[PDB]
Amino acid sequence: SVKEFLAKAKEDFLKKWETPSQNTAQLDQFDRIKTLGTGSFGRVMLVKHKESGNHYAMKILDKQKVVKLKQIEHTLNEKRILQAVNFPFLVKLEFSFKDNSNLYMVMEYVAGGEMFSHLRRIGRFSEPHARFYAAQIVLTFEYLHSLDLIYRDLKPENLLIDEQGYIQVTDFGFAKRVKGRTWTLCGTPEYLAPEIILSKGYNKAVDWWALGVLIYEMAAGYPPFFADQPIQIYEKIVSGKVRFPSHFSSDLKDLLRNLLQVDLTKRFGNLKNGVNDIKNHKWFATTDWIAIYQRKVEAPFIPKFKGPGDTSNFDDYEEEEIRVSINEKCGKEFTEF
Amino acid sequence: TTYADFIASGRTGRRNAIHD
Ligand SMILES: CNc1nccc(-c2ccc(C(=O)N[C@H](CN)Cc3ccc(Cl)cc3Cl)s2)n1
Image (cartoon, rainbow over all chains, first blue to last red; front, top):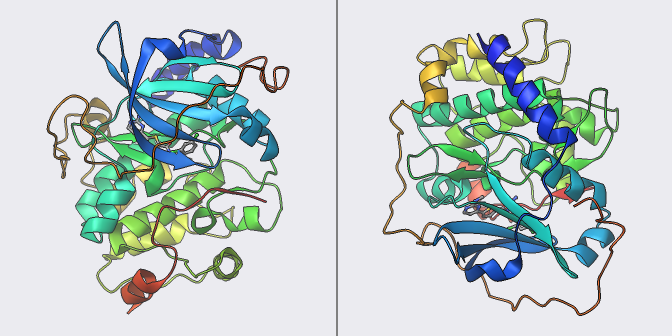
């Protein structure tokens, strides 16, 4: 049963959670090839591990920039959580270390690009395409929530597509292990549950709302609430009125009406039956959850590939020399990293 | 159309995380 598999997953996580890996590599073991993306406080680069020839994605986080965004705890959470978890649909952290200037997280390289890019290009996904991705998120959250983790940043920009067309969830910058309620206003505006915007204190149910945004964006080709400025977006979410495209099936509208629910006594994922309220919904009737976990379902889309360290499924970014300062920066802030 | 309204908006590129 899920219950029993989750049980043993918990025991696995807690061991690593309590006794975290630290300092398992160094910058000079890696050759740096290309930038694959950029964020608030750093970049992700394709790199090659010199002594194995294995390719990795290396996230470089500028410590000074981290400190000035007040993201120190958030960054310690990310690395602490990522070394401890293990599930098919989550990026794998192989190595981590730090120097005078930066933090580094070396993860398995995912060659197929971000969902975002394939979704913007083709426009929208078919409901079966969208459902194949949704299922994988449904399982990943059931995993994470079972370890008392909240993810807090679901969106196509964060879903990497592997060689087999399956998802890897990347960027745990806002993931947090919390049993009670939490308060940080963080995430991405289009994806914020109304209780976050309203500073009420909130819980894992914000992830189930974010799933509603994603299913909707995947199937409509745009999100349920958009405007040019964030403030405009928050007003639409707090009204909460959703219109569905004429092409949405009945089942999809109904699954969404229950995910994009302001009332928490009513939101799917959050009720007495928990995740089975979602998994047993009619929209998922065709889904075989076990074959999904096992990766035996045929992917509706296989990204195009051309070789080992190929980067054409990612955009091009301006390169920037990695400078490492001769003085140590923010030592005590990042001691445990 | 809603599509056309989206495509014409400034929020079709990769969307930054916020904090506060
Ligand atoms: C894990 N394996 C793998 N394989 C190929 C490509 C990639 C990535 C490309 C962009 C990524 C990312 O997390 N970007 C964030 C999206 N929310 C944005 C971000 C945040 C912080 C920093 Cl330092 C850098 C970036 Cl790009 S991860 N990862």
